[PDB]
Image (spheres, coloured by chain):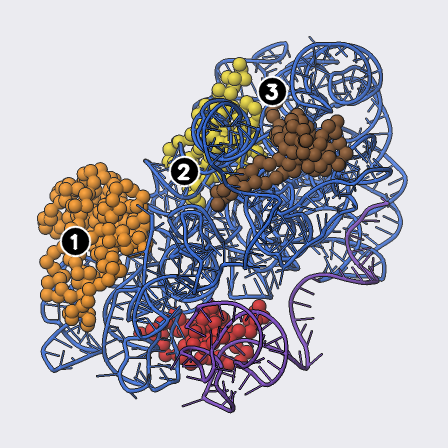
Chain colours: A red, B orange, C yellow, D brown, E blue, F purple
RNA sequence: GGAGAGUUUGAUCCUGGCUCAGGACGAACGCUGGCGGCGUGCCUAAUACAUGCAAGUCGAGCGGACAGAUGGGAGCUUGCUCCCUGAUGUUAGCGGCGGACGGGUGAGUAACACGUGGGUAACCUGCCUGUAAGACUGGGAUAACUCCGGGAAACCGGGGCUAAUACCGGAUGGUUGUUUGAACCGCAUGGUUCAAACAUAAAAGGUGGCUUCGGCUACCACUUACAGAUGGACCCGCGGCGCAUUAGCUAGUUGGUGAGGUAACGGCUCACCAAGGCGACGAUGCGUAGCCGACCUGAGAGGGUGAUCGGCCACACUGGGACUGAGACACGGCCCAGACUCCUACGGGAGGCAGCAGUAGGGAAUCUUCCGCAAUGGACGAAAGUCUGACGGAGCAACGCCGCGUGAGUGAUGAAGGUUUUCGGAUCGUAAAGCUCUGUUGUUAGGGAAGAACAAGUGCCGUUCGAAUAGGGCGGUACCUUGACGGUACCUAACCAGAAAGCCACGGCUAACUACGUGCCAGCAGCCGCGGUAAUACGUAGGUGGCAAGCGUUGUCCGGAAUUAUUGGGCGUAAAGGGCUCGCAGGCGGUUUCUUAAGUCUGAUGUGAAAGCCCCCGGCUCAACCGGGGAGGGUCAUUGGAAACUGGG
RNA sequence: CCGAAGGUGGGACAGAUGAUUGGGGUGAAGUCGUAACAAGGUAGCCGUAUCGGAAGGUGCGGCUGG
């Protein structure tokens, strides 16, 4: 992070953009299933693209209102 | 706004008429004509709260602030909140008999202008104090919608007095909640906002 | 030094002025010594309210009003009472 | 027009050893903000003895005054009860 | 004014934590986005700043200037060019006043910094009032201006000249000091008033008008004293923090005498002595922090916060210093040292956005290099005026709150189409279309406020000055003026449902369900926990529900949580009785009575500013908001009653 | 004389980092035993000493929570 701390975050939605050395915005969200992981990567952030093929739960996972 | 749908879901005639529940008394939808289950305490309080707020068409910001201001008055709490939503000016237009719904009475206060004690009111949420002679200006003096609702004769409630031609609506002392609504259960809504 | 001066109160587009005994040093809306009543400009008529005796009390210890506060004193008529006191 | 009255205490002498002065324990005692029960606190003041007519264990009145030195703001009034 | 629910088990009751349902943000993020009002908008780097402004003003203090031409003449080409001192305007410099206010920031600061209450016989206070005495008589310089000389500049030095309301002598003075008498009064030092003498301590003129030219007067200014007012100082009671895995800390520290110093008391500073001072009621040390009115939550007690607004504080690139001035040890002043940026002719110079805009950086993250001094303040001026990034406004951002919207009445062919179906239909559902109709908003086009009162200039009238109807002050009228916002809010007419809805959830808590795909994969999740081919929990569609130009997630507060229990919990076995004693400090105290009045209760007085919460009315089209009026809040100070209880004798 | 900064010096506190190390937690059906729960096949536990790959054993005293 920008304070200097390495934490394991989580990438919630289905199929993610990220590589190594990717800019990531992190919110606080506990992932109970995987131990040691207590943040979420905000989807729709600086470089973490909005997820693919999603229409329900639009604002979470980042995707724009597609078209109709 | 469908507004038949609101009535058949809430299970109450929100106009108060033989319409909108005859031929289809179940709630809406694909899960409606089957035997629905009874609601919990939460569901009953929501039903009664939304019976009242879908009678008057209020958003919960105004509905909560009138709940609070009614708490700042004296007496019984849920009676005073009924009284404040029966001082609301769309309700005044539809209970003087100048519209067939409260949406038509909303459009009368919003643009098809109507007047209190003089100049004008463009605002449905105007709380109407007593003693206030409510009429229309000489521009919209008698036009087709107010003309129809004058031709149709409803009862004037005893907390109102209404004229046909001069069309001034004047008031009395206070609307007692015996007069206001038989179907809406108050003090389940006080309990709904008690939590 | 000590000056009876208007003090801004009210909303943005609708001003209001409390006629307020303050110092020239102190800020306009800030600290002040005592107040006399009010001044509504934005009424389409008149409506000034001056205490008219405690204002008179501050005038005599030495507190010279601003121009608009002075002519409000003249409108209620305290500068004539002050001139009658100096002619006394 | 009698002028304004200065603060006055009564107390108890801790020490005599400073030159022409004493210190005095005022035992006024007061209650809490929260639990309400009334607890005690001892406040020792520096007070001037211009005659040095004091002893340890002496009930004495003190007057407040202008600051007589560092930490001194008090003087004697009436030496009430002497130590035994 | 007080709601609970899931989860330890095969089942249960307790204990017990965890998790959820709420309200809030100076919030950010994601999806989405219509307006109007009012508020708010670098929380992070007290990081660094390009540029533009943010403090000047007075020609009624002064000298010199620049123009200018009322008349006066000048030389000729009809194109022009001066020289006398009219008004008239312009202001480098002296000088006075201001720059110490206003605006920013919260780094420091854990103690008089602040809040509250006092005390000053221990104090200062320009400008402002009000009253009383005055304002005499001279002197010598200097800026400007020139003439040199030195400097890259910054600028500096030398000789000349000149004025003041500049500065300095001098007279007269009820100050101040000394000395001697009194008189009365306290709270220890002491206080107030009277008299005398000695020693000094003032001051300035400018404008207008009257005129016998000596002067006389008003206004402003000057000096001294005494009050008021205002601002400032210092001192004390109480109060608001975490750690004891910080227990010992001080030596100008703790007192004295004397001196200096200060506006003043004081180890504030110094000499000389004494061995003191603070301390488990938490000294010292470390960490954190501007404090408060208030703000959020809560039934309240409390807990958290210290944005905006308002008071006090501290700071001004870092540390130190003084100067001047009434007041600074001075944000846009100075001198020095350090770092940084810049210029240099290498000798030396300049700078300080934590003023309003803006830039770069840090960051999840917060705005315009705008218009105006019209209004309210300020500074100066006799005033007109000038200055004013305070302030009025304007712009950007749904950042918040509030209000109006995206239609309305009628409508069964329950149209098409979606989804589902035991294929009878059910549903999206009167919701579309049909008919009728409004125009808030959208747009076009006209009309157009309050915010303005004034100042100043005239004319009156009363009045004080005056040698006087001059002339000026003071008061009342009676006119003529003044808008950045802005042809903005606002009103009126025309037109079309036309431009205007999304977000989240649907197992339970928790309102809201089906279908298709997946197959312990993809994934969801706050918890219980879903999903391994019949998934109401995953993804999609339909539907429903919640709200609504918002919605959801996050981060922190508070509640829920009686889960720090004072209100309001516990310790046989669930966590918890010291292994037990002797005891210091502390806490608690059987009975009768007298007395006291610290606690307690009660009264009066002051005060706890304004805004805020609350009550009551009023104005904005309602609302938010504004405004008026009141209430509330102290273990607060002084003062007066009670004596049951606690305490004292 | 005072005096900011700077200089020298010896200590005090605090954060990193350090070959190596010691205990701790969590993890794919790993290895060795089976110490405890029943009289858990030697009743268990508490304190203490000692020994032992390891749970543990043994002594002494105490406890029933036999």
Q: Along the line of sight, which residue is nearer the eye, E138 or E32? A: E32
x and y percentages locating residue E351 in the rendered image: 70, 53
* Residue neighbourhood size for the residue with mark 1, other residues' Cα within 10 Å, grouped as few (<14), some (14–19), many (≥20): few
Q: Secondary structure at mark 3?
A: loop
Would residue B27 be found to the left or right of residue E332 on screen? left
Q: Residue at x 58, y 70 (%)?
A: A4
- Residue under label 3, please give it: D2
Q: Position of residue B72 (x, y in %)?
A: 31, 43
Residue that badge 2 annotates = C42
Read off the residue under disc 1. B183
Distance of label 3 from label 2 (alpha carbons) = 52 Å
Quote the CA–CA distance across marks 2 and 1: 49 Å
The chain to which mark 2 is attached is C
Viewer-nearest residue: E208 or A51: A51
Instruction: Measuring from the top left, give residue F9's x and y in whole percent.
Output: 83, 62
| Disc 2 element | loop
């Amino acid at each position: 992070l920008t304070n200097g701390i390495e934490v394991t975050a989580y990438i919630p939605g289905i199929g993610h953009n990220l590589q190594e050395h990717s800019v990531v915005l992190i919110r606080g969200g506990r992932v109970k299933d995987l131990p040691g992981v207590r943040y979420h990567i905000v989807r729709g952030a600086l470089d973490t693209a909005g997820v693919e093929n999603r229409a329900q739960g639009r604002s979470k996972y980042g995707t724009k209102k597609p078209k109709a | 706004g469908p507004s038949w749908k609101l009535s058949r879901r809430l299970g109450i005639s929100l106009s108060g008429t033989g319409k909108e529940l005859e031929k289809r008394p179940y709630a809406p939808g694909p899960h409606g004509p089957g035997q629905r289950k009874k609601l919990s305490e939460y569901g009953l309080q929501l039903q009664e709260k939304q019976k009242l707020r879908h009678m008057y068409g209020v958003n919960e910001r105004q509905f909560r602030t009138l709940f609070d201001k009614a708490g700042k008055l004296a007496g019984k709490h849920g009676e005073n909140f009924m009284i404040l939503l029966d001082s609301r000016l769309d309700n005044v237009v539809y209970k003087l008999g100048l519209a067939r719904t409260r949406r038509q009475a909303r459009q009368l206060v919003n643009h098809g202008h109507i007047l209190v004690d003089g100049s004008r009111v463009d605002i449905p949420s105007y709380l109407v104090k007593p003693g206030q002679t409510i009429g229309v200006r000489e521009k919209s003096r008698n036009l087709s919608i107010i003309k129809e609702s004058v031709e149709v004769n409803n009862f004037v409630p005893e907390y109102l007095t209404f004229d046909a031609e001069k069309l001034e609506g004047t008031f009395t002392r206070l609307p007692e909640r015996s007069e206001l609504a038989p179907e809406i259960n108050e003090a389940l809504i006080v309990e709904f906002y008690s939590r | 030094a000590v000056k009876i001066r208007l003090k801004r109160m009210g909303a943005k587009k609708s001003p209001f002025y409390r006629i307020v005994v303050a110092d020239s040093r102190s800020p306009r809306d800030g600290r002040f010594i005592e107040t006399v009543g009010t001044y509504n400009p934005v009424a389409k008529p008149a409506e000034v309210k001056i205490d008219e005796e405690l204002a008179l009390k501050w005038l005599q210890t030495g507190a010279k009003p601003s121009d608009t506060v002075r002519n409000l004193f003249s409108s209620q008529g305290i500068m004539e009472k002050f001139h009658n006191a100096k002619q006394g | 027009s009698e002028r304004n009255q200065r603060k006055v205490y009564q107390g108890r002498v801790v020490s005599d050893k400073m030159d022409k002065t004493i210190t005095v324990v005022v035992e006024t005692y007061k209650k809490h903000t929260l639990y309400g029960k009334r607890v005690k606190y001892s406040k020792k003041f520096k007070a001037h003895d211009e005659n040095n007519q004091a002893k340890i264990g002496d009930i004495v009145k003190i007057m407040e005054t202008r600051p007589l030195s560092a930490t001194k703001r008090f003087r004697l009034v009436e030496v009430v009860e002497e130590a035994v």
